[PDB]
Length: 49
Length: 49
Image (spheres, rainbow over the protein chains, first blue to last red):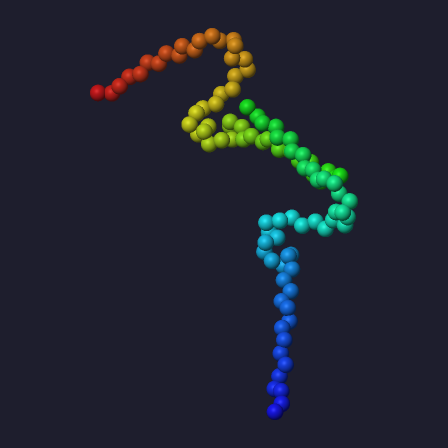
């Protein structure tokens, strides 16, 4: 008796930026997020009457 | 700690003479409307028989 074949998988590598889900996001690579304490975005909405 | 963005609305308005509402009115801008108190224009309208 003898073997006929040995078969395995190749893991399908699907990253974030190839998917269409990044249409709902804005992606920035940030080198040292270990150093950051806080983030901030400041709006100023002027309302006419 | 960071400051990642700073944003603000700018209000633009379509004025009166650019709307479609001026298709239902005639606009004759006067220099100082405080001069005349009351307009009392009288019309003589004659029907046919």
